[PDB]
Image (cartoon, coloured by chain):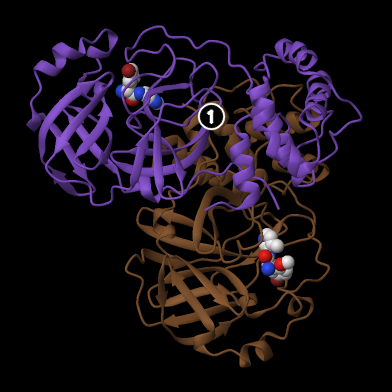
Chain colours: A brown, B purple
Amino acid sequence: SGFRKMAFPSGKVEGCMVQVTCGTTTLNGLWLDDVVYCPRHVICTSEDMLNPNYEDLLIRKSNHNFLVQAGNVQLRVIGHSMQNCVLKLKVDTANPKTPKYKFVRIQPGQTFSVLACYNGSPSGVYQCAMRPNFTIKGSFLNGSCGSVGFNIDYDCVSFCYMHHMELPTGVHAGTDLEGNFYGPFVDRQTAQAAGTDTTITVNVLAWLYAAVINGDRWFLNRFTTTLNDFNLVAMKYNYEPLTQDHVDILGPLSAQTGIAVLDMCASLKELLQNGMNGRTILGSALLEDEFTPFDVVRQCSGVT
Amino acid sequence: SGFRKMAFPSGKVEGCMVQVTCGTTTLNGLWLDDVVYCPRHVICTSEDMLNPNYEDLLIRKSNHNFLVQAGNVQLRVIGHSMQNCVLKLKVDTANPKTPKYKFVRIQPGQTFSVLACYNGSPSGVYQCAMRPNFTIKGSFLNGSCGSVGFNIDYDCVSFCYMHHMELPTGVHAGTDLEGNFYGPFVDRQTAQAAGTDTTITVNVLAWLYAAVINGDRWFLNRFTTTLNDFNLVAMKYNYEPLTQDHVDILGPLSAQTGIAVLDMCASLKELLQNGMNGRTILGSALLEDEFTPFDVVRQCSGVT
Ligand SMILES: COc1ccc(Br)cc1[C@@H](N)C(=O)Nc1cnccc1C
Ligand SMILES: COc1ccc(Br)cc1[C@@H](N)C(=O)Nc1cnccc1C
């Protein structure tokens, strides 16, 4: 009973968080095995951020300039390199708390948990989605850079995001753990505006299935539709076009509830056209799009 | 930038979760020092739950009947006792992962994080509030009993909740860590309906302050009100009456934003009377009440 925006337990990730300082800049790092990963802008001054030449700024830095502290103990830096927009600091000690891990580059629409940190210390955990415009709507303040996003498959942590910056619009941009930005963003204090933030249709449908499972059924109607007809409506409302791949991914939820995917689409179509009329669905007055079909099945089945 | 429903990092609590089995019933336990705490209904069969005599059911149980497993290792039970609606299983090994902890009985309106578990394994973490009717709107399935709610003050974990049951209404009831239920609920499969779920006014105001801090200011108006006038409106909308204590707790947010508490009340009064007119506040289309004034300051200041 009940449906919440649930994050993965963060313990495995808390054991990897460190503080990295270079000059007067302090941010978070991720310590996995004998490498600490962090945003390369740790080498910048606030003056440098307008147009930094990272290769040139990095020439003036040695191993002893990167101060890495895991809790209250100092790690010895024996190597450093830049990979895309991240620095990799080789330390002389493997993190004894290193979980089983992978680095993944997620697709827009996929969700993940963020462990927001400041000065190497965890402050909170929340659930996110990579928006279709490759931004994330996070909760980050100055000093949160280097905080990571991840998913957990039983004992394996798949790191998918590292926080780098906030756009002047209040949304967030960052990289995968290879240092490649999601979207067109660059690690520079320049005019960067995000594209259209479209709604993740397959996630809204998954959340409608979660609502039916939990007893919120008022929006179910007597109608059906086709993918092409639904997509005419999805386009008008800045919703992602629904494909056969999305329908197939919703198959298990359709089977569990007995509500055909296209009938759920017709319910969604009427909700777009008429709104909620002051009603709520799973305690929300808007259509939620940050639960994937996998998230709904996981939460509705009790996977640990 | 940004404002999210953020939970505390769960690592310190994950290290305390164990599985407790008695007969054919398995649920979660909390292992702190050499004691495992769990709901007393672990001694019941599904037949017993209609009207259980816990003292009588417990007479037929010995230490060796409580199977406690921490991950994959078995804990040896050397004593058991019932305190209100919880069992305390004395084990021969202190949990090496026991954090600094306290047991607190929270007030309605206060928020906390829940680490939902099944079979002693964490599945997710989310943020809750103790409703004014003493229920929590959680996300729990069969096997989640014994999952706990907590707050963290730097290194100290204050456990405030242990999950015991779901009401036929889909909301949740449980106890503090002394085994006393929040509200009038009893651990019996009987007709238990929750009282009026009123809105936590002081939390809605705190969240309006969080919105102004983050740039969502459309709802600010040219009006002010008085506590008595505001409370006439709060009563009509099933909002908690606002007291001078609530105004005082909002003092730091009022000071940070320069918006007097009673002016924010007048903004809230117009939002109640007119609705949002299809607009959103911090990505919500309803007035959020599960952030306390302490939560807003913590999130808006970056406390770790
Ligand atoms: C002004 O700081 C930057 C400018 C450009 C870049 Br690349 C990076 C920063 C960085 N020092 C920072 O702290 N970023 C950030 C991210 N999320 C939330 C808040 C803030 C401010
Ligand atoms: C039917 O189970 C009970 C009846 C009464 C009581 Br006291 C306790 C239970 C318990 N066996 C249970 O699993 N509870 C529960 C809690 N949250 C979500 C889901 C469920 C079912």
Residue drawn at the location 80% of the way across and 14% of the way down: B229
Q: Amino acid at mark 1?
A: Gln
| B292 sits left or right of A8 in the view | right
Identify the image quadrant of residue B191: top left
According to the picture, the residue beneath numbered tag 1 turns out to be B110
Q: Looking at the picture, how far across and down is residue B197, in whole percent?
A: 58, 16
Q: Position of residue A130 (x, y in %)?
A: 63, 55
Chain of the residue that carries numbered disc 1 in the rendered image = B
Which type of secondary structure does the marked residue at label 1 adopt? loop
Residue A219 in sight from this viewpoint: no
Q: Is residue A278 left or right of residue A255?
A: right
Using residue B138 as the reference point, say whether residue B272 is left or right of it: right
Q: Residue at 75% across / 47% down in the picture?
A: B214
Question: Which one is nearer the viewer's eye here, B66 or A181?
Answer: B66
Left or right: residue A125 compared with residue B248:
left
Against A52, residue A292 (above or below) is above
Q: Is residue B47 above or below residue B288?
A: above
